[PDB]
Image 1 (tube, rainbow over the protein chains, first blue to last red):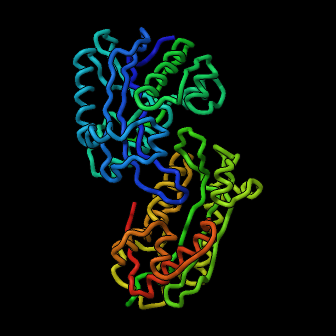
Image 2: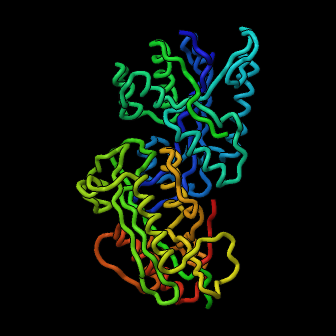
Image 3: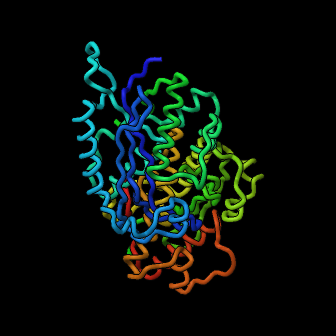
Length: 214
Length: 213
């Protein structure tokens, strides 16, 4: 099976959250992880991780610290989301200059092996379609335009293996990949999502864009 | 004090929820309540209630059934969300045929004629700005355009009384309205939210649109 993208960037956001019934607050990203997956070798050639300091609700709840495993001192040393997006773009620009990566849906010219097509992968459409999207609009921040299209890996998992998975853990378990300890979060969840994408590629799944916000 | 809107429609959604240690992002509406408040008389002239059958997670968790008071058989008898908006629009169309209500944007003056201005009121922006909005966008359903602007009663309470309320119950307690027992849910919570809005009108608060999409 021939893949369209030479690299995927897998992202699994962690954010503030509460489950106190009908009290509803505004959620802010607290961890911004990304792993660069090589669709030809299967390895992780580069990683990005930044803890984001919340501004509207800077105190992490016990439910949130229990769910994400993130301690208070980590978001206290972290940077606001605005600075985080600048750091992430610097990382994107770095991996472009190193691996000759562009973000395109296809080359309308004969293929040149020097250029590499890359795409963003998330588990659900929640990361780049809900979490980062509706937070940038509410804080009037500039969202990088290359995060407006991605690959919903859960939807890709459903139509490929022809079954409905019960979360990222359930999907990994059904294909024989079992991890130990608590459910991964942040950079660990991103690495495991990239493992699932690599397993799907080995099984012959061609990763295609599933959602666009344009 | 002269009010801008002649009627308010108060909405307090109930939705699926879990507390099983896992990450949960998409919630589905399971109760669709709405009360029509008369801002001049103080009465509730009409009500709407529909139990919505969830599709992505049709089995209500025990944490959800306990928190909302909704039993599994009620959403089993309920209708999908798509059908629910059609019933809600028929109810909107019905109160239009009876009370001559219109929904208009950028209203800088109370109506002085036969036509009556109405607006939607919810506690916080979560109901019409997060819950219904994301669920319609992910399910590719057509959301009624008149649900694109509303009155955040929590924000209106904060800037009017100049104090931080501890939830809808905390807000009611601070204005002398005290309830006992479990936290209300669904249609009961909508009536209690409309009670708060009526008292705020009595204190002189002019209800204004706070959010528009």
